[PDB]
Structure formats: structure tokens, C-alpha cells
Image: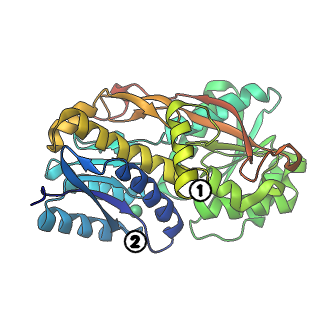
Amino acid sequence: FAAEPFTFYGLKSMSGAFASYGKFADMGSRLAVEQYPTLLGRPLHYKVIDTEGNAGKAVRRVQEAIAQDGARFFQGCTLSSSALAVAKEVGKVGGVFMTPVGADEITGKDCNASTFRWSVPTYGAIRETMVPLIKLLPEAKRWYTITPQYVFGEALLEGAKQVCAEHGIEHIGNSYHSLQEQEFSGYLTNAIAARPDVLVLLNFGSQSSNALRQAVNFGIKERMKVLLVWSAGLDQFQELGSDVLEGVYLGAQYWHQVDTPLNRELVKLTQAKYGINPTYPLAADYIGSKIILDTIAATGSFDGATVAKAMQGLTYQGPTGEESIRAGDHQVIKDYYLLVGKAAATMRDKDDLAEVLSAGRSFPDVSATGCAL
Ligand SMILES: [Cl-]
């Protein structure tokens, strides 16, 4: 007679508009779980929960797993809305939830004892792109933003304005657009009229790809520099290709070419299991899942509250290098990157699409986050 299985739950947007993200995030968790055929002597099972990229669906599926199967350990979500909602449910039963989403609140006003987050949020993304770019481009004084009229976009814009004030450059204007907007010609001509030195795209996902592609086809790169603050890294770069990307400045959470102990391992793993290089969604869920399983293994405990406490202040090898979970706000302290798209001729392989120009840690003091644990 075998031991009772223990189940780890991946919350992934397997269907709907974010199916591609979910596919690779799921691949990431699966790689982590496969490294533990058993965990503390018990067979380790993985169960995917489809959030459908919808907060309501995420909550109901998590609630069912908690009630019916005694679920406690979760990793994933694509959307901040889903993660905020899920965080409350996991928090109520004293489980553990690690997420890659980017809303600042996850580790701020809405933090809880059960919830941890790997990605750098808007505060750091803005600072690790714009600040090093200002250093690279001392004569770039006039900065124009294009922003989705939505909470994540406004947070980025809020940050871009703080940086402009702090560093003596000029925010010369802004164009808002809806999350559904497919047409950017009008906002691009607004930018042209403003005569910027840098066009800053504060949109994200499919929309930023469409915006950037229109900007480039419009002739923008011949007139001014372009920065996409919040890019999806490799998988987005592959879709756009070097003709679009060449010379464009890009912010990202992860880059497969960075030489670190865990990244070397991860690249070998994805090459041997899927025949590809790791992308951001894959890497974020790989590490988020590995931290949880490693800490269960280290503590000898399946108790959520015990594992969560052990994760506070934990230092470990991660995809960006040596990373630590800050105890006070449950934020992973790690690099965010500024890259620039490469010219086709400088590429060594199909994935050699961008060059890292800067990497660094920008995080607020815990006392400024609103997180009170
Ligand atoms: Cl989601």
C-alpha cells in the first residue's frame, strides 16, 4: 500500500485570451514538480487549475480544490485581478500562494501572510529602465508616454512622472488609450507633434506588440528612441522579430542568456524537455514552484504557515542570480533588465534577439509599501 499523494496546484490561464502565457507557465511548474518524484516520502502530484484568465473562475476553482481535495499550495495566475482574489482564499485557509503577476498591491496594501510574488512590480520596472536609459542618452530631455487608461497603466505612468521629476527630464505629454484599442496612428501622430526624444510605451501584452509594430511601420525609430517598459521578454521578441525590434529599448523580468547557476540548469532542462530556450512565463513559474517545493523539502512540513514563515527572508539561486524573498513585504528581490533589440546581423541564433544593457534592483522600503504583516 502506497503513501498518500501530496498535490501541488498550478493556477494557469490554459484557455481564453491568455492561453499562450498559460501554456508556458504550466510548462514551468511541470519542470519543477518533475524534479521531485516524491516529496517527504509521498508521491508528488501536479494538478492544473484553469483560471481562464478570469478572477471569478480562478476563485471558484481554487475554492473547490480547497474544499474537496484539501488543497493548500498554489502557484500561478496570469492577471493581477485573479491573484488578488486568489490570495484572499488561500490566506483564509493558511496555505501558500506564489505568483508572477505585477501589480504593486500584491506586496503592498493587499499583502498577506500566505502570498509571495516573484516579478518586479511597476515601481522597479520604471526605475530599472528609465534611469539607466537616461544615463545612456544624456541628450534625451523630452519624453512622451502612451498609456492604457487602466490601473496598471496608470501605475506605470505615475512612476514615469516620478522619475522625470527626480532626474531633471521633461514629461512633455501623454496619450491615453483603452485596453481594447487596436489602432495607434492617432496617438503616434500626437507623439510626433510633441517632438519627443523618447517615446515611452506603457502598454503591455498583445497590445504593446501591436503598438510597437505600428510605431515602427510608421517611421518612429527614425525620429526618436522607443522604450517599451514592460515587455514579455523572449516570447514577445520572437513574435516581433529583429526588423521591428532593432534599436528599441525593452524592459524585462528574465533573459535566458544571463549566466547564473540556476539559469544554466533551467536552460539545460528546457532544451532537454522541450527543445527550446526558457521564456519569462516559463521561468517565473518554474522558480516560483521550485521555491515552494524546496522549502517543503527543507522544513519537512506540509503546513502552509510553517512553509510561509520559512520563505520569509529566504535566499536561494534563481533565474536572475542570487535572489532573496524580503521578509517584510513578501517581494522577491531580484534584477529587472533594460535590453535593446539587436540588428539581425549581430544575432548568433534565432533567440539572440536583444542585448542586456543594464540590470538592477529597485524596490521601495517596506515602510513605504503599505504592507503590514
Ligand atoms: Cl489568471
What residue is rendered at 85% in x and 43% in y?
A: 346
Q: Amino acid at mark 2?
A: Glu
Label 2 lies in ligand 1 vicinity (Cβ under 8 Å): yes
Q: Badge 1 local density, few (<14 within 10 Å), some, or many (20+)?
A: many
Residue 126 higher or lower than 9, as above or below = above
Q: Is residue 59 above or below residue 332?
A: below
Question: Does residue 25 appear in the picture of this structure?
Answer: yes
**Label disc, if present, on residue 52 of the rendered structure:** 2
Q: Position of residue 178 (x, y in %)?
A: 58, 66
Residue 149 falls left or right of residue 329: right
Q: Specify the amino acid type for callout 1.
A: Phe
Image coordinates of residue 302 in percent, x first then y, are 16, 44
The reply to whether residue 108 is visible in this rendering is no
Does 168 sit above or below residue 242? Answer: above
Between discs 2 and 1, the one toward the N terminus: 2
User: What residue is rendered at 61% in x and 64% in y?
Assistant: 206
Disc number placed over residue 204 in the picture, else none: 1
**Side of 204 where 35 appears, left or right:** left
> Which quadrant of the picture is home to ligand 1?
bottom left
Residue 146: image x %, image y %? Answer: 67, 53
Q: Nearer the viewer, residue 293 or 230?
A: 293
